[PDB]
Amino acid sequence: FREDCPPDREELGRHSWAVLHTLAAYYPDLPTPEQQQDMAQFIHLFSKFYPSEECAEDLRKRLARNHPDTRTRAAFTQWLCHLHNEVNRKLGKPDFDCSKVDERWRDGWKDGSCD
Amino acid sequence: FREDCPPDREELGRHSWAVLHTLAAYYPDLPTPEQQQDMAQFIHLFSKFYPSEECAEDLRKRLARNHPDTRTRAAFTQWLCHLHNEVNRKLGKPDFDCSKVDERWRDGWKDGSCD
Ligand SMILES: Cc1cc2nc3c(=O)[nH]c(=O)nc-3n(C[C@H](O)[C@H](O)[C@H](O)COP(=O)(O)OP(=O)(O)OC[C@H]3O[C@@H](n4cnc5c(N)ncnc54)[C@H](O)[C@@H]3O)c2cc1C
Ligand SMILES: Cc1cc2nc3c(=O)[nH]c(=O)nc-3n(C[C@H](O)[C@H](O)[C@H](O)COP(=O)(O)OP(=O)(O)OC[C@H]3O[C@@H](n4cnc5c(N)ncnc54)[C@H](O)[C@@H]3O)c2cc1C
Image (cartoon, rainbow over all chains, first blue to last red; front, side):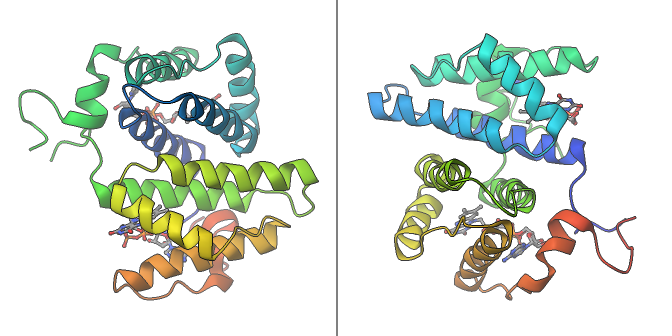
């Protein structure tokens, strides 16, 4: 009942996905080489500091199997959506339909339900 | 009424502070030089990608006035709390008492109200 408490593993995850997907959503469609490098490093460093040890370890192993594609906004928003679906699948959750990532994290549902 | 919508500036901020303060809260008390460097760069790169343009610009100017202290968990959790209070003050919000940052973001209130 008290809101202003340290987030548990689940609440930190929902915050963290919101942050990651929203950052990805506004990433350039034609990012410069430095931007492409900087976003790869950001994600690397996120994985180093993520504070749930079980989450961060599994994450670092995934990232070794699957390097972030930061070539464009389209590639990177998709990459990250596929990343998040691995974790969903691991945890017994359904796949999120990655064709919806712009509606979900940038533009709002096309039916106007976020307006 | 629909939860699964792109966060607005305020909702992204509350997610982002939760992430930043929770990362800081679990940062080492005696971090290695590389960890100290990595956390400085993480914060730098966060400021590059933060997607509210007005927020990110003001943030990058603050960070130029006030470089992150990543020497220890104590110094860095305090630094970040002072950073967040600048933004609070800017926006007409009261100061958060920085002596409470461990209770708020790591340990829970000492009265046990998060238990
Ligand atoms: C990097 C990272 C690693 C994690 N690793 C673990 C772990 O190893 N073990 C563990 O127990 N927990 C882990 N978590 C926490 C976990 O992934 C969830 O955040 C938590 O279980 C709560 O899940 P949820 O059902 O509320 O929705 P979440 O998975 O938090 O998702 C939040 C919202 O994102 C949207 N969404 C869902 N899937 C996608 C997608 N693929 N692409 C774009 N949007 C999507 C949906 O709207 C959903 O409601 C991790 C979190 C992060 C950020
Ligand atoms: C890096 C960054 C820069 C931003 N810049 C702007 C900007 O320029 N203009 C703008 O309008 N919005 C900005 N925001 C959004 C803004 O700071 C708030 O997140 C948003 O206004 C909602 O505020 P809130 O009252 O819900 O609480 P928030 O400020 O989001 O705080 C969330 C919670 O953190 C705790 N808290 C509050 N202060 C501290 C503290 N100092 N230390 C530790 N914990 C604390 C409290 O429990 C509070 O409920 C920024 C957000 C971030 C993350």
